[PDB]
Amino acid sequence: ILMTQSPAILSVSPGEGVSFSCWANQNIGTSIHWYQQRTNGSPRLLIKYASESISGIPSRFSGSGSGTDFTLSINSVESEDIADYYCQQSNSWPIFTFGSGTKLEIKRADAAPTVSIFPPSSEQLTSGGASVVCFLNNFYPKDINVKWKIDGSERQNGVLNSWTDQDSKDSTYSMSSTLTLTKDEYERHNSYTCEATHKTSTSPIVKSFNRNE
Amino acid sequence: VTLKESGPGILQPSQTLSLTCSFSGFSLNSFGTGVGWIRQPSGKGLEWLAHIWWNDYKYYNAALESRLTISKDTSNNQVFLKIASVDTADTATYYCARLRLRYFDYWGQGTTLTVSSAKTTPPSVYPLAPMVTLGCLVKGYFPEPVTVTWNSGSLSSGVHTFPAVLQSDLYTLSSSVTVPSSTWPSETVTCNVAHPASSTKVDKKIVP
Amino acid sequence: LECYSCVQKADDGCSPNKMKTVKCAPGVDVCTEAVGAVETIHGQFSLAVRGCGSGLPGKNDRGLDLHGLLAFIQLQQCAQDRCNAKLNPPNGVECYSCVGLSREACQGTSPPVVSCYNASDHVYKGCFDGNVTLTAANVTVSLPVRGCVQDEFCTRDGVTGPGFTLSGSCCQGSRCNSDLRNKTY
Ligand SMILES: *[C@@H]1O[C@H](CO)[C@@H](O[C@@H]2O[C@H](CO)[C@@H](O)[C@H](O)[C@H]2NC(C)=O)[C@H](O)[C@H]1NC(C)=O
Ligand SMILES: *[C@@H]1O[C@H](CO)[C@@H](O)[C@H](O)[C@H]1NC(C)=O
Ligand SMILES: *[C@@H]1O[C@H](CO)[C@@H](O)[C@H](O)[C@H]1NC(C)=O
Image (cartoon, rainbow over all chains, first blue to last red; front, side, top):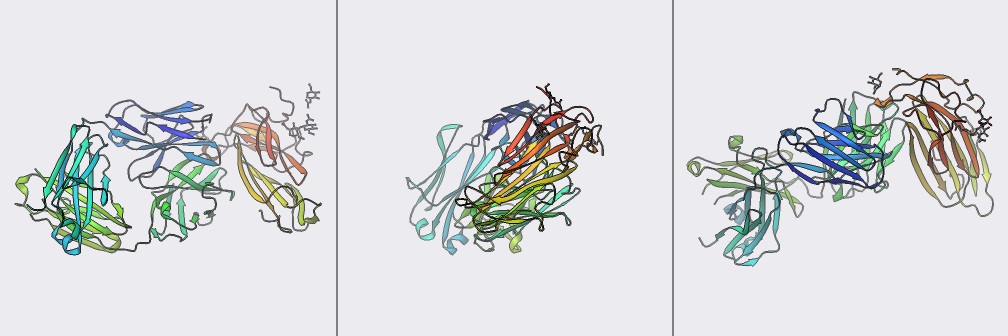
């Protein structure tokens, strides 16, 4: 038995009526259960046997379906319903299988990132390393591409990236990009640039510095 | 009804993982009761591993049935899972949850396991100097986690503390803070980084 | 090749002091051991067969669920001598209960009556009558099974495992399951 959740990401505004799909390749009767995992939290059982409600669960969470297609619905989305939602089948008891998950995201107006680049610190250069950081803060949607260029030439190696979780207050995403060189390599090139292609602009937003000035 | 997982926190590859689930508020003698183990790699989905029943029957994820053995002591309210020959892919949060016949109604908070051969290492903390946005870089520490605060939490809006990434087995992250330009360098901005596993706390003032 | 040979019918047939050691016919290369435990919400019993087998070495375990009757089967086949001894509040409804009794006891209105309950917070409000069968070593063993189940309307339902079947019918009302061998569809 194969279980496909859809969508993977479900961007929604507070107060809307949202629906999560979980599809079985086969007929599994009513043997489906739904779990909520808030970020940094344990999975929490929401719905039992397709549609049975769990005690102590808000009344806004309801589920439905039988056979192959199953749905979890939130009548009125609240701020603490931002979470991952997993289905699990019990059709092949005692073998249990979970879905891939549906991550509930908050919609916001698209916003371009504020990009900020930083040289290596004086402390780090003493140690023999040279990491050039670029922050891209407060943007939407999460899809973003960072391209590193040194004196025009692209830089393939030495790059580490990290995305944040969606922000609690403004619903933006943020990203760090780290280019890590040796001290000797860093003191042999002049310009360090981080360009970011995003949906807010056709041409990428570029922040840069020169190690000369 | 509660479940509490405990485990070793960090292991090197090849070692045996031994997990304990200590539970209360119910019994593993009831017909249909079971306790299972589920793990989640960070940022990834949940995977069922194994479950043990009141009548001592045990079920395994067949992809791991060679590595897994689950057991229980009903007298002490404990279920154990040991996973032999740990690898990097066993880096996950491991949850125990109780099986009412077909679903997991009650789960623990989870125990986080890192499989790495790296040893406990304090971080190197570097200032990032250029409204204006400032930061600090925390490079080369093990294990997770670090906590990063600015002015001990007094600067809280405009702070982004990024997930750690692995570079050659050691973690690195950065934190950024965005302030009005009228407050720096006129007022001080300091990064405060605590690493609980190594007993370390470091302040780094960022100066232009 | 010498194997333990014994058959267990919810009794002691496979007990230390009833087990026989048998020698297998030419061309049989494995000893078998198959235990099928069936669990009702009021008890559990086991069928077991130990003897000379066929086929390859291996282990085969399976859990089965028929409207809340659980069955657990372990079937192991080795290739060494004598290797095959490695396994071992009320709700409204009342049902007849057969959990180890012979087809003699388990007939008609003879079996004990049990009070169903909502085991593991699932509703057990139907009654069941059927049998369990476990086949291995060119021998077959079966006993009747009766108890509470989560379905009041099954007719000749069944689950299957390796050499193992658990089948029967369900019904509604207390002690409906007096005798459902004839129940039509
Ligand atoms: C489970 O038990 C028996 C298996 O022996 C099933 O079949 C009938 O059982 C009676 C019992 O002595 C035999 O005399 C009959 O010959 C069997 N049927 C036939 C067609 O010959 C029985 O039906 C099963 N129980 C239920 C409720 O299905
Ligand atoms: C099952 O039985 C218990 C005890 O009677 C009761 O508290 C529970 O609500 C019952 N559930 C249903 C669905 O009948
Ligand atoms: C089952 O039904 C058949 C056909 O009506 C009859 O021959 C037989 O005796 C019945 N047995 C019982 C126990 O009712």
